[PDB]
Image 1 (cartoon, rainbow, N blue to C red):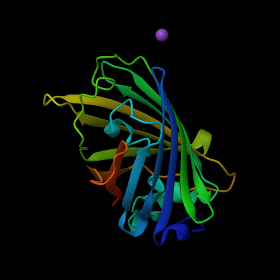
Image 2: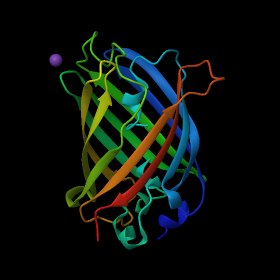
Image 3: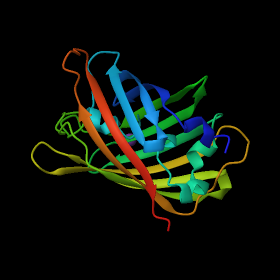
Image 4: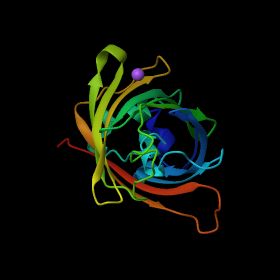
Amino acid sequence: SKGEELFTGVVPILVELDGDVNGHKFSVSGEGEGDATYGKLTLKFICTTGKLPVPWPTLVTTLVQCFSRYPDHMKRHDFFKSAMPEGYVQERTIFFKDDGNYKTRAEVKFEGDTLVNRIELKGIDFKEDGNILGHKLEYNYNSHNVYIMADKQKNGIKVNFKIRHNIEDGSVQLADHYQQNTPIGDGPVLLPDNHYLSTQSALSKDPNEKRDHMVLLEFVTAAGIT
Ligand code: NA
């Protein structure tokens, strides 16, 4: 409705994250655009503090599900856009198997015509020689499904899914994601029936960019109903 009409065209996106993983502090700034009509996201992220101390793929999920394409028949299940423009809080705990965890809190809302994702990330219990702090993950990203359920008690949603990061030896580093989103405003939101978002992502590098960075192209579509 009101929220849905804010995404019918191309919307500029800004992402700002401050992180601390095992005491390694860093900041990331991202810019790009989203076109929910095609579930399309294009963004470029920059580590503004120097070298990123964790692998870029591990930050992908943290670094705007309101850009998902919801088929017309599923639009009544789109919580994310319904919370706009006031926005929502997105919180996650990401458990890296046999390693540490990230806890994140983000506020996603409009500032003017720009969709902004402001994030604080805290990582603890990482192994200094593990796949994360040791940078043993390939610079790529597998397709992932996100499973969404209503959470009535918080007037929001609960989300869970698995991400499998590719290790450079051919193995896999699992990152189990637990997520909750709650509206910032007190207006009504769409509480959905169970469904999922199917996402595909491609990571690349800007050949003229010398700062540590990540270019991302992502397509996201809601599914699972009718
Ligand atoms: Na402890």
